[PDB]
Image: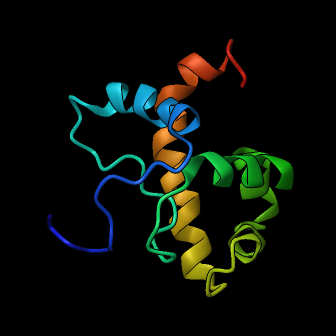
Amino acid sequence: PRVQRLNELEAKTRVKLNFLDQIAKFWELQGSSLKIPMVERKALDLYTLHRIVQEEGGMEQTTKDRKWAKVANRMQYPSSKSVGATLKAHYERILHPFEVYTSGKVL
């Protein structure tokens, strides 16, 4: 378990969340904790949260705007600079090594 938050299986929409299992195959030999979105909200929905960040302006431009506070308001987090920085750093470490794929395949 190694319990930080309440989680076990978690995948409401399986085929859409399976996109997170595709990138999990990229982090399988790294051992790094992937598929950890709603670190506060206790559940895990990176798919819909990734659409939110994109409609705010994408992870890169929303970092320049520093609107990660307001991205946290969209799913009703306790909107802190710390909470926004947790989501920011988590996107930075995961998408920037994997953008070798998303460069030509911008989904």
Structure colour scheme: rainbow
Q: Is residue 48 left or right of residue 82?
A: right
- Residue 57 in sight in this render: no
Percent from the top left, x then y, of residue 92? 54, 47
Nearer the observer, 83 or 46: 46
Give percent across and percent down for residue 88: 59, 59
Residue 23, how many percent across, how many down? Answer: 44, 29
In the image, 14 versus 33, the foreground residue is: 14
For the view shown, which residue lies furthest in the top direction?
Answer: 104
Query: Is 2 left, or right, of 81 in this rendering?
Result: left
The number of callouts visible is 0
Residue 60 is situated, as x and y percent measured from the top left of the image, at 72, 45
Quadrant the C terminus occupies? top right
Residue 22 seen from this side: yes
Relative to 82, say whether 61 is above or below: above
**What residue is shown at x 74% (from left), y 53% (from top)?**
53
Residue at (63% x, 22% y) in the render: 102
Q: Residue 50 vs residue 65: left or right?
A: left
The residue positioned 57% from the left and 69% from the top of the image is 85
Vertical arrangement, residue 36 with respect to residue 42, above or below: above
> Image point 20% across, 28% down: which residue?
29
Identify which residue, 101 or 74, lies in the foreground: 74
Give the quadrant of the N terminus.
bottom left
